[PDB]
Amino acid sequence: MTKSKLPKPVQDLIKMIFDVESMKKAMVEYEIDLQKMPLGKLSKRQIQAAYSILSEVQQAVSQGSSDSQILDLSNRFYTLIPHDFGMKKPPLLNNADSVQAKAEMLDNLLDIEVAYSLLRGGSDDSSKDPIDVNYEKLKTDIKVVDRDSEEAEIIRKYVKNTHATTHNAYDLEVIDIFKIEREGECQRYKPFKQLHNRRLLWHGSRTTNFAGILSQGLRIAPPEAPVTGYMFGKGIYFADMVSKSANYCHTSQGDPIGLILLGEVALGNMYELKHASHISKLPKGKHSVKGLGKTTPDPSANISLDGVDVPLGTGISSGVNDTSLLYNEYIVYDIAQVNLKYLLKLKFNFKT
Ligand SMILES: CCc1cn(Cc2ccc(F)c(C(=O)N3CCN(CC)[C@H](CCO)C3)c2)c(=O)[nH]c1=O
């Protein structure tokens, strides 16, 4: 039992990422019946089948089919994924809002299954630290960034300047800044290295999703998933406001620690949109979608970190009139266009 020699912040990141109990709390959060469907019985093909029902609902809504099939499909969904709503009525699956809500849950279920499968697979060695074994499963080089360097100064300033006044429920404190290097991702990203308009953007996610996020990278919703469950289609979503992405950590009062990503995203030509557009492909010659937000990080204060633009400017009006987005959103539809650079441990201080 050789005790791990990894730095203490990296060891804590490993423990927090592979926490089986956190995976169970996330499933209870969705009111999933863990007695009828324990974490060990959660299956990949089960999740894709549930995605198919969501897509079947989407098509039934789109042709008028009949709302009673939609009733049957909704009941079929709750049979496939056993829930426990105690005495209340389970939410019906008859409108686009409920399809998005269940697609989001399946997104988290998909990454939770990947994490658990990682843990219970491969090899195990009694003489090895579980932290050391779980670290190697991530297939990622993780190094703690020195607090006093210019990387951390830029990253801290990115956090400090782009917390929107709208997201007033909490404030953010940077605990740890990690430099991350997924195996093979640098080679995969090379075909996009010298594309224009490369920005450093945030991606917030639930803590449980990060075992899959680090082992497999950011992925696109599977083909079974309904394209109308996502505002701008089935792509990878980023933000330039740290608080916009931190909201997608789903941090609570009982679990105030969150994980957020800083990724280099090859945006190229930007299909600028102001409202929903459930697309699967992009128009020829366009490399990403930008949701136009009312507030944008002041473009006068942009800096370059390793030839990548960092929109750490404070929030100002964008001049866009008829848009449905409070803040900007960046979406790519090819996973090769993303190169993950930094991983942040954030403490959420909720104001009460
Ligand atoms: C605006 C910034 C922001 C938004 N949203 C919401 C959101 C909405 C629709 C989306 F398609 C995705 C997204 O990118 N997905 C969907 C889930 N997963 C399916 C395989 C993937 C995850 C990586 O494996 C890819 C994310 C976050 O969650 N975080 C953020 O920072």
Image (cartoon, rainbow, N blue to C red):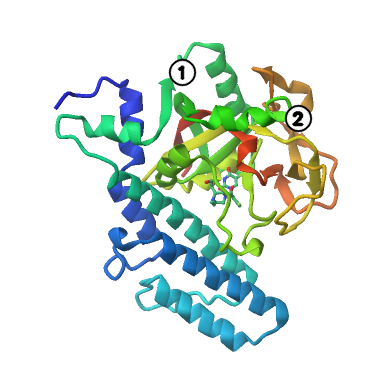
Residue 297 shown left or right of residue 20 in the figure: right
Q: Which mark is residue 197?
A: 2
The residue shown at (56%, 63%) is: 224
Residue 188 spot, x, y in % from top left: 59, 33
Residue 10 spot, x, y in % from top left: 35, 26
The foreground one among 167 and 138 is: 138
Mark 2–mark 1 distance (CA, rounded to whole Å) = 26 Å
The foreground one among 100 and 85 is: 100
Q: Is residue 183 above or below residue 165?
A: above
The residue shown at (51%, 36%) is: 260
How many discs mark residues in the rendered view?
A: 2
The residue shown at (37%, 47%) is: 115
Q: Is residue 85 above or below residue 275?
A: below
Q: Nearer the viewer, mark 2 or mark 1?
A: 2
Q: Earlier in the sequence, mark 2 or mark 1?
A: 1
Q: Secondary structure at mark 1?
A: loop
Residue labelled with disc 1: 145
